[PDB]
Amino acid sequence: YIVERLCACCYEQAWYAKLGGVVSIKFLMERLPLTWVLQNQQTFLKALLFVMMDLTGEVSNGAVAMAKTTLEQLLMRCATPLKDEERAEEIVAAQEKSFHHVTHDLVREVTSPNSTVRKQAMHSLQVLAQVTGKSVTVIMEPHKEVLQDMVPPKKHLLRHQPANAQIGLMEGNTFCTTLQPRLFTMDLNVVEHKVFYTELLNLCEAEDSALTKLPCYKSLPSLVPLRIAALNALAACNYLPQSREKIIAALFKALNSTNSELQEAGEACMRKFLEGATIEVDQIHTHMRPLLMMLGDYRSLTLNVVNRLTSVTRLFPNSFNDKFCDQMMQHLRKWMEVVVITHKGGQRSDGNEMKICSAIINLFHLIPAAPQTLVKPLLEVVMKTERAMLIEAGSPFREPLIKFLTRHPSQTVE
Image (cartoon, rainbow, N blue to C red):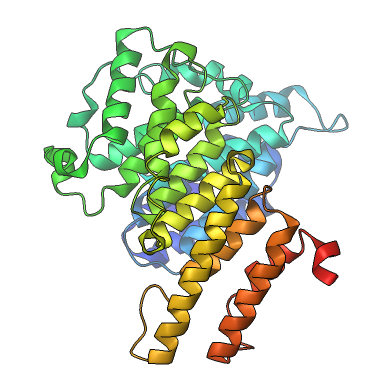
């Protein structure tokens, strides 16, 4: 009755009721013995995860972090292997049964449409596989019966599912297909996987003007998380030779865009994609061609294009050459002259004041093709700008310049 009434507080509406319920659960699992907390771990987990499922979308006072910490403690407690001095026929059986049930419910809630509970379940599975000294797959291999119809959409026309459910399905597919050994192999041969891959490609490659026509996406405020999830799911399929060019094309299209958050998501997915696949300089040039071929005019530069340059350089150091370094130095000199002119004019702040020059300077320390000779012209232009603006302590060019100078200490100090 104690556990019933106390964990029942987790189902009340108010947030303080949930907080008291989780506090009582923590007290019960910390003070009382192991043999008893195991058989109640099912109800404890259910209640303390329903707390999260219900508190999403409303103000709360640290209840989410407290619930996450309590979940971590309960999982690392009940999952801890029993030492030989305490192993017995009843405690071992109770632990095994509680572990089975908890893992079953966790794999069930993994594909839930809520993001917070899904991330919490993923972290719990990871830490549980870490503690038990086993892989996540072998632990989920018996439990994948629940996800036989979840990871494969069964050609359910995901376009009919809501945006949050779609994002949840994408994240579940990413998690289940990115373990040490993959639980489900997206062979891209059955009609189900084929339809799923085609939907992923059309979602991550189409345009917003046509993508917003769907009713499921008509009410979305940003539509960026959907594209991010689509890119993440598409990168997890780096085991299909005959169907790899489209993945690279989509990842590069996402790596060259006029948005910052999506550019970062695309570069992250590419870095994750390169862990299993490889890309030769041929297709690198083929895909970055529209990114280049426009730098001829220094005015064409901007924060987005320099960020894309930085990303493609960080992902492929051997892609750029010394000629590109000289062109970048010329563009930097031009932009520094423009900045000096604008500062002498003293009209008003703009969006091309310092960030562009800082990014262009940072580009050098990431390109290994940058020669030692580039230190002197860069230092000269930096000194010219500093003494034209008379900004010494607040100069934002110090950090990237020092980052580059550290690459050639011999020439620098000399």
